[PDB]
Amino acid sequence: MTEYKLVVVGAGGVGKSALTIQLIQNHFVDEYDPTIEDSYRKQVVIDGETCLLDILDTAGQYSAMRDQYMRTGEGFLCVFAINNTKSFEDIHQYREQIKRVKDSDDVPMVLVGNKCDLAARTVESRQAQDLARSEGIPYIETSAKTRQGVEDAFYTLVREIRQH
Ligand SMILES: Nc1nc2c(ncn2[C@@H]2O[C@H](COP(=O)(O)OP(=O)(O)NP(=O)(O)O)[C@@H](O)[C@H]2O)c(=O)[nH]1
Ligand SMILES: [Mg+2]
Ligand SMILES: [Mg+2]
Image (cartoon, rainbow, N blue to C red; front, side, top):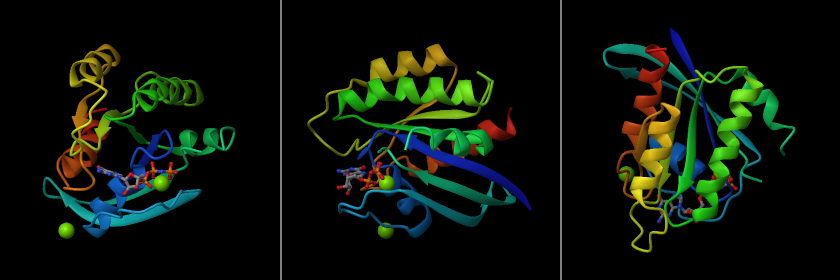
């Protein structure tokens, strides 16, 4: 079957793992558990097509160790947290590193604003929007906790790969 090589990147603690675990294991981790590098492979049906999601869950903490997984990566979830301004700034750097490593500014990518269940927001949707719009990528807000937007985000990425 068709495989889609997805890579989840972003600053430490933004909820990259929680997002992936919600998608694959239908629950919210709700705990401290930093990632080194984890891989999930799940057979799904998206828009009637059987496919294998091969998802790489990466470290927000291993910078030269990033090139290799960006090289093979097919599409990228670029995650920040809407209560964490710094993480939104960092996500600029992730995108630039992906573009550089892959020698392309045409790599399938979704900008993800996670933790949208939290009231104490510090990153307005509008600024994330403008940034996404500027870069030619979709913007989707998620809550790994309530599952809001989680399938939207991952499936949109898959469709962005099919549309490439
Ligand atoms: N309220 C809320 N908390 C979330 C959400 N996603 C993750 N968290 C919480 O935020 C923390 C970080 O989650 P985690 O998934 O480990 O982040 P990460 O980006 O994978 N971290 P790392 O880069 O170190 O692997 C945990 O306490 C987790 O339960 C979310 O959507 N909402
Ligand atoms: Mg993690
Ligand atoms: Mg559930």
